[PDB]
Amino acid sequence: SELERIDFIKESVDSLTTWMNEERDKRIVASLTNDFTNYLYTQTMNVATIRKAIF
Amino acid sequence: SQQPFRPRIKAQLSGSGVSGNTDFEANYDNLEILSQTIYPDAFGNSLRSKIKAY
Amino acid sequence: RFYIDETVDAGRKSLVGVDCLLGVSKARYQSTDGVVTPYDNQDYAVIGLVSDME
Amino acid sequence: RFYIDETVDAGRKSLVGVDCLLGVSKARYQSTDGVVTPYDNQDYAVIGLVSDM
Amino acid sequence: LNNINFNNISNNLNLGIEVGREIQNASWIKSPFFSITGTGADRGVRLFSVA
C-alpha cells in the first residue's frame, strides 16, 4: 500500500460510498419497475404518449 | 519512500586531455553513467501463540 | 454505516465495509379484509412507459 | 516491521508477524545508452571461485 | 558502431518514474433520485423515518 502510494482507507471509503449510492438507487428503480399493473407501450417516445400517460 | 531503486556508477575518465595552449574543446572527455534497477521484494513470517492462560 | 478494520492479517491488511438496512417497496396496498376494490393489487402511483431501444 | 495482533480468538490468542521489503541485487550495471564499456553487463565486484567438493 | 539511435526518452535509464498521489474517480455522476426522495407526503419516493 505504501509502495504504490495508495491511501487505502480513503480511496476505499469513497468508492464504497459511490457503490452504496448506486445500489440504493437500484433498489428504488427495481422496485419501481417491477410488475407494472398499468402501462403504455409505444414504438417511439413522443409527446403524444406522454400526454396520454398524464391523461 | 521505498520504491524500485536505481543506483548509478560513472566510469573512470580515460582520455588524454589537452597539452599546453590547446583548448579543452579539442579533446572533450566523455562522462559515462551505468545503471541498475533494484526492485523490492516482500517477505515475512509469523508466529501464532496459545491461549493467554497457557 | 461504515466499518473499518485495520487488524486484518495481524494488522498487515485492512478491510473497509459499508452496510445499509432499508425497506424498499413499490406502493401497492392490499385489502385488510376480503373485500376487493380497484386499489387491491395495483401500483398506487406508477404507470409504465415502454418503447423500443433506438 | 513487526505486526502484533492481540485480538486473535476474541483477543485470547495473539499473532506476531514480521514483514520486510528488501531489494537484493548483485551489482551488475548496464549502460544507460549505447556506449559499450568494460562495466557493461558484468559482475561489478565479484569473481567466482568454483571447486570440487 | 555509431548509427542513428531511434530510441525515445523512455529508454533513458537515468530517469525515474514519479507516480501521482491523487487518483481520479468516476464519482462525478449523479442520478436524479435523491431529489425525488423526501419525508413529505408529496414525494415520488416517500421516506418513513421509523425509529
Image: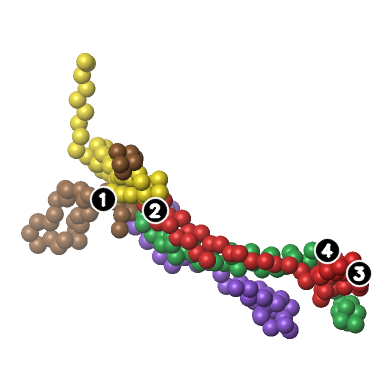
Chain colours: A green, B brown, C red, D yellow, E purple
Corner quadrant of residue B45:
top left
Quadrant of the rendering where the N terminus of chain A is positioned: bottom left
How many numbered marks, from 0 up?
4
C-alpha separation, residue under disc 1 versus residue under disc 2: 36 Å
Q: Are marks 2 and 4 on the same chain?
A: no
Q: Is residue C6 above or below residue A38?
A: above
Few, some or many residues within 10 Å of mark 3 (<14, 14–19, 20+) = few
* Whole-number angstrom distance, CA of label 3 to CA of label 2: 58 Å
Alpha carbon separation for disc pair 2 and 4: 45 Å
- Identify the chain of the residue marked 1, using the numbered disc in the image: B
Q: Which residue was labeled with disc 1?
A: B7
- Name the N-terminal-most of marks 3 and 2: 2
* Residue neighbourhood size for the residue with mark 2, other residues' Cα within 10 Å, grouped as few (<14), some (14–19), many (≥20): some
**SS for tag 4?**
loop
Q: Which label sits in the foreground, 1 or 2? A: 2
Residue type pointed to by label 4? Asp
Q: Which residue is mark 3?
A: C35
- Per the image, the residue denoted by label 2 is C7
Q: Chain of mark 4?
A: A
Residue C8 located left or right of residue D48: right
Amino acid type, callout 2: Thr
Q: Amino acid at mark 3?
A: Val
Do the residues indicated by labels 3 and 2 lie within the same chain of the protein? yes
Disc 2 element? strand
Q: Of the residues tagged 4 and 3, which is closer to the observer? A: 3
Q: Is residue D40 above or below residue D47?
A: below
Q: Nearer the viewer, mark 4 or mark 1?
A: 4
Badge 2: chain ID: C
**Which residue has dot 4 on it?**
A35
